[PDB]
Length: 236
Image (cartoon, rainbow, N blue to C red; front, side, top):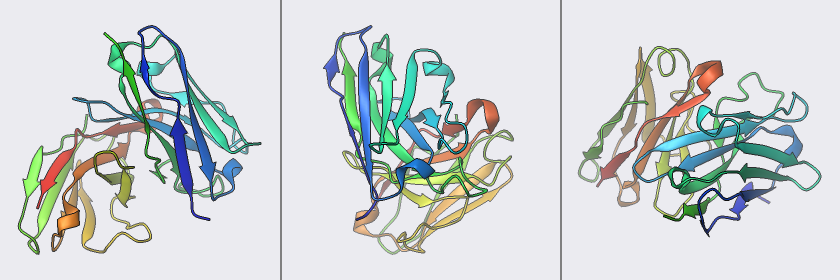
């Protein structure tokens, strides 16, 4: 099959309005995985919106301070489809909204930490925390290093630092997880590392396809869950 996530429902909407985003999964046994909603907004970086776990765990959804009380996340295990309900939409809510699968099933110890298989996202336009060097460049074949500096409560408190690669209009993609692991099919020239409060990505032997925006993320404990950097344009 392949794992596929398709988010729908976005569009130009007037303020204070309500909108439901759908995410239809395929290719895995939907019921066994947390599903997380993320947001990419211009000027801001990537943001965690909320999380719903497998019903084999609790299922009670967790949201983020921002949307805490006006968004509501939901699942339909019978049709393998997660939902994001948005209420009282302000223009500061305009963004691309992404759907995500926990890297593991509810069985695994390391569940509820890393997310993968992001969809393309659906754009919502409404009418009317980790430090990351803005830019980096190199020549093809040369090396490059990206920094992601957070605090004790995030990068330096855990072994859950991810890096995503983002091409405009395309689904963000896991390059590195758990600080230094390469998912299946990420070339060993992408390298993860950390020390204290600062993580590092290293792209050895650059390539034309390697020119992208690179976002870093860390688990940030029970209260904040996730946090991101503002992204880095690598230019080859």
